[PDB]
Image (tube, rainbow, N blue to C red):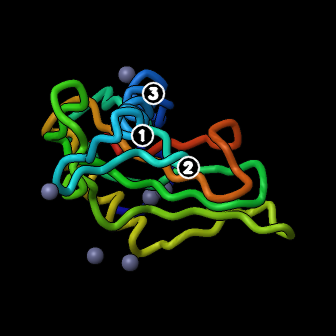
Amino acid sequence: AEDGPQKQQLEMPLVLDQDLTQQMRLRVESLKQRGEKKQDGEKLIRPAESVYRLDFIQQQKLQFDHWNVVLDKPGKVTITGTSQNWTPDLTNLMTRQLLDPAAIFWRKEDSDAMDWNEADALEFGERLSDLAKIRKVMYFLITFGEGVEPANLKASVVFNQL
Ligand SMILES: [Zn+2]
Ligand SMILES: [Zn+2]
Ligand SMILES: [Zn+2]
Ligand SMILES: [Zn+2]
Ligand SMILES: [Zn+2]
Ligand SMILES: [Zn+2]
């Protein structure tokens, strides 16, 4: 197997889930509004976090090839996955449903080139292939570091068709 471009691939984007990202925003507010307290080991979405959705156009015969994450302005972003068992409509996201490691990308003031934590990013990347089989859709929580926003990001995953 001599790697190259001739191989067939599938790029699947991480679309911003505004409805779901909003649902979690209320939740945090509701609890302040009602001076109420959150469940045990519950994950409350933060202002710097937004929920993203990844739709697996294919589930079988997948091999993680590489992440395709680009920031158009100097900053940092963390892509953390959620359990393929987490039912966003039925239950509140629990801290234990956040996957590890998270894939972290960044760009600096003098570079137009992205750098990241290769190891962890690959670990995470590898898992995605087997997660595609649990269910057709998957969600992630993307934490935008200071200076960046959803407008500045283009995230996707490239898989090799087997
Ligand atoms: Zn949605
Ligand atoms: Zn408690
Ligand atoms: Zn490649
Ligand atoms: Zn390759
Ligand atoms: Zn690890
Ligand atoms: Zn690590």
Residue 45 appearing in the image:
yes
Lateral position of residue 4 relative to residue 100, left or right: right
Nearer the viewer's eye, disc 2 or disc 1? 2
For the residue pair 45 and 27, the one nearer the viewer reads as 27
Residue holding disc 3: 22
Q: Say which amino acid is labelled 2.
A: Ala
Pointer 1 residue: 9
Whichever of callouts 3 and 1 sits on the residue coming sooner in the sequence is 1
Separation of marks 2 and 3 at Cα, in angstroms:
13 Å
Asked if residue 70 is positioned above or below residue 88 in the image, the reply reads below
Q: Which residue lies furthest to the front in this view?
A: 35
Q: How far apart are marks 2 and 1 (CA)?
A: 32 Å
Please provide percent x and percent y for residue 55: 34, 29
Query: Residue 4 or 136: which is nearer the viewer?
Result: 136
Q: How crowded is mark 3: few (under 14 residues within 10 Å), some or many (20 or more)?
A: few
Residues under labels 3 and 1: Cα distance? 33 Å
* Residue under the image location 77 percent in, 68 percent down: 108
